[PDB]
Length: 352
Length: 76
Image (cartoon, rainbow over all chains, first blue to last red; front, side, top):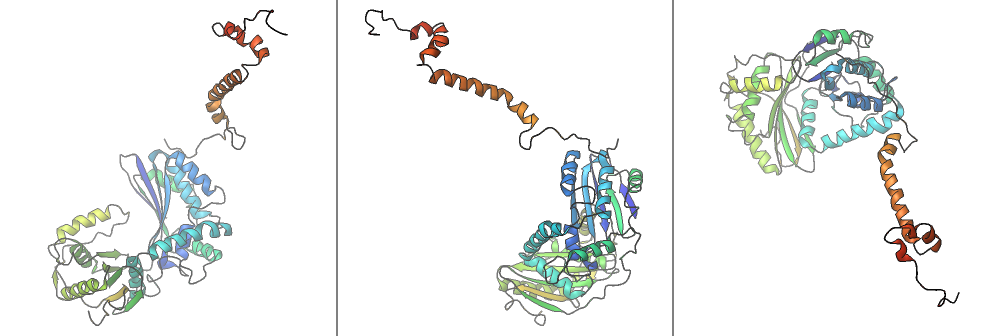
């Protein structure tokens, strides 16, 4: 129960209760996604219709976001009604209904919609494949529920009792008086949540290299390389991601996307090259892997990536505060490779 | 200050009709009553009982409606 807030002289506050309860900590495949879609449903006291129709007249909305690690319960509001939203997030964490007619009518159709939308995009399919073959049972769990194993209502109640525990979450209010926030989080149900253990492990996530997966897909064709990185090597792959995204690289015209996902014990640098026909993807990713195995000078992208890191980092509540100063050179070692789409014309891992 | 509750009453309603909608609709209901009364004044104009009671009391169109045949060329 770590309460933090950064005050400001503005009109809109945001509250965020972050649990360490995303797909990485899911016991079955997709329990985290179903709990996230079960977040702002009706409680034991206040319904879900009364929640929306009161919070609109007070002037703020809610949003539950599922991450690869967290579950963020965010609430945006006009500043002078903070205890309502503190008590509403408290009621959601402490007493949700978990009704079976709520599982069949709201949570399962919303999750099926999320899964259909993220199924239609081969970049998210390849990102999930790259996760699931870099790390296997940890972060390489599926992000979304698809129904390949039966997640029942009792499993969501069990996962919520495991995850919604008092030492597992953190309360963070952008533009909130912090002393008032600490007074309002106490005298509420965040202090009556169970003080369970924190699910954050402090060890390394036991990655795997040289793996290759191939998914057939009707539509666009992407090919993706992915490197699991550790805590000492986070800044280098950060300046690499902003180098290949930036206009300093000669490979930015070929690369569709390149991003590093950072965690408190490691990260995954994912590079996607996406096009309509597989010959362009083949030529592009052969050039990418060749000119990355040949070394790159990541020294020019340093002041640019300080800017882009501050841009990305002002939104989040937990900065990692990377170094960016000792980073000079990069040379591509081993890497994991997925190919999605016209999979008989995208190259294999030997040909790269 | 800080507001924790949303203070509201439950209004007055009969399922579909509300008192607020009735008060918002009521002068146009009076206008439709007047329009239907003018419609009855149209479609009952030839009625000589309503001519005798109402329409011959009109200033400029009242004596216009009554006839001027003497009781020498009326058969009955």
